[PDB]
Image: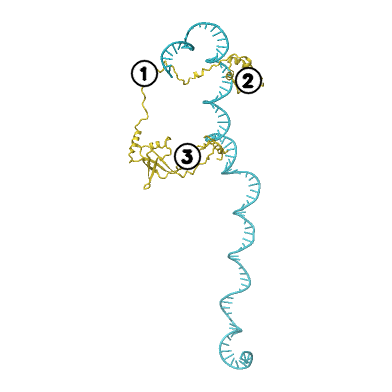
Chain colours: A yellow, B cyan
DNA sequence: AGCACGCTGTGTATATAATAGCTATGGAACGTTCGATTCACCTCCGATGTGTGTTGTACATACATAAAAATATCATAGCTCTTCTGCGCTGTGTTGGTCGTAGAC
């Protein structure tokens, strides 16, 4: 939504039904900033999943404020379901969460009324006071299933080797350079699509062509050889013989290189 | 039902007249646009002229100070002649006694 900045005409009232002020009533919500490993971030950010269903439970043991995640069994079985939420900062300062929503376009002292401000709806989702990180638990039987998977991270290669053509080299070189095979592709056949347009015309008489030239000059005073030729469908030799009698080309004016009506016929 | 087979059309090549129409091409002119180059103005050091602080002077007064000199004041010697003091003398106040008397009670 591109829009002009520093608008003092209050045009945002008419074009934007939603208020431009920042919503702050959600800022009192507590938000835990959590850093996840590769698998939990992979399965907790995909758009084909996360339909609002429950993914786990949070257990906070108050003996030492130990936070654990007990994941549900609906996701997988090879992954662990018990995790430790370590807190690297019990109090996190100067960190908040803000969200942006698109607007509805339907229905010294020196200042400049143009700053190119993009208006977007903004709202503080809450306040962050806990920076969290989720580690897999040591005692889980599936914990090794993570570690080997991590050992699978450095082991697999994402690139494949080059492919070697194992057939006879003459069959491979049959298509190269000198070949009987004419090209059958239609990619950039500019000469095919431009040389097929041919104009054919006859020596149609002088009175009708001069009347046609007068009609085009009445429609617009300035014309060219190509536009008049495609408008009247006449040969260049016959069209030139009629233009110089009743019209002339401009040599020094702002509309130069264009055929225009003579000043004697201009007042007609 | 759809691809193999047969048939036909088209393009290849040869010459050769005809015509109109289309197109490539060289050149000349000119508008458009973009990069290169230079002007005016500002700034910043540098020369300059010019302006001002300092010193000294002139002209012709006023003005504060102050010193040599005439002079009023005074300190003091001289003098002189009027008073103070010591000595000589003497004469009258003093002491004692007697007796009238007079004034206090």
SS class, disc 3: strand
N-terminal of the pair, mark 3 or mark 2, is 3
**Location of mark 1 (residue):** A169
Query: Which corner quadrant of the image does residue A254 belong to?
Result: top right
Q: Position of residue A7 (x, y in %)?
A: 56, 37
N-terminal of the pair, mark 2 or mark 1, is 1
Which chain hosts label 1?
Answer: A
Q: What is the C-alpha distance between the residues marked 2 and 1? A: 69 Å
Same chain? Circles 3 and 2: yes
**Location of mark 3 (residue):** A99
Task: Say above or below: B34 vs A45.
Answer: above
Viewer-nearest residue: A55 or B87: A55
Which chain hosts label 3?
Answer: A
Q: Residues within 10 Å of mark 1 (few under 14, many from 20)?
A: few
**Location of mark 2 (residue):** A215
Question: What is the count of numbered marks?
Answer: 3
Query: As drawn, is A167 to the left or to the right of A245?
Result: left
SS class, disc 1: helix
Q: Say which residue appears at 48% left-offset and 38% top-offset.
A: A100
Q: Position of residue A19 (x, y in %)?
A: 53, 40
SS class, disc 2: helix
Q: Is residue A57 visible?
A: yes
Query: Which corner quadrant of the image does residue B77 belong to?
Result: bottom right
Q: Is residue A178 visible?
A: no
Query: Which corner quadrant of the image does residue A86 belong to?
Result: top left
Which chain hosts label 2?
Answer: A
Q: Nearer the viewer, mark 2 or mark 1?
A: 2
N-terminal of the pair, mark 1 or mark 3, is 3
Q: Say which residue appears at 63% left-offset and 15% top-offset.
A: A206
Query: As drawn, is B53 to the left or to the right of A62?
Result: right
Q: Position of residue A20 (x, y in %)?
A: 52, 40
């Amino acid at each position: 939504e591109v829009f002009d900045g520093n608008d003092i005409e209050n045009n945002e009232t008419k074009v934007y039904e939603e208020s431009l002020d920042l919503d702050l009533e959600r800022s009192n919500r507590q938000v835990w900033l959590v850093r996840l490993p590769m698998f939990l971030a992979e399965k907790w950010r995909d758009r084909n999943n996360l339909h609002g269903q429950e993914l786990g439970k949070i257990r906070i043991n108050k003996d030492g404020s130990k936070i654990t995640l007990l994941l549900n069994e609906n996701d997988n079985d090879s992954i662990p379901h018990e995790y430790d939420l370590e807190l690297t900062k019990k109090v996190v300062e100067n960190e908040y969460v803000f969200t942006e929503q698109n607007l509805k376009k339907y229905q010294r002292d020196r200042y400049i009324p143009y700053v190119k401000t993009i208006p977007k709806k903004t709202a503080i989702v809450g306040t962050v006071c806990h920076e969290c990180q989720v580690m897999p638990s040591m005692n889980d039987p599936n914990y090794h299933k993570i570690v080997e998977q991590r050992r699978n991270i450095v082991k697999l290669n994402n690139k494949e080797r080059i492919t070697t053509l194992d057939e006879t080299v003459g069959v491979t070189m049959s298509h190269t350079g000198m070949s009987m095979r004419s090209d059958n592709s239609n990619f950039l056949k500019v000469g095919r699509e431009k040389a097929k347009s041919n104009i054919k015309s006859i020596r149609m008489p002088k009175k009708e062509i001069l009347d046609y030239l007068f009609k085009l000059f009445d429609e617009y005073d300035y014309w060219s050889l190509k536009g008049l030729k495609e408008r009247t469908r006449q040969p260049e030799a016959h069209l030139k013989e009629c233009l110089d009698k009743v019209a002339t080309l401009v040599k020094k004016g702002p509309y130069a290189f264009k055929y225009t009506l003579r000043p004697e016929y201009k007042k007609l």
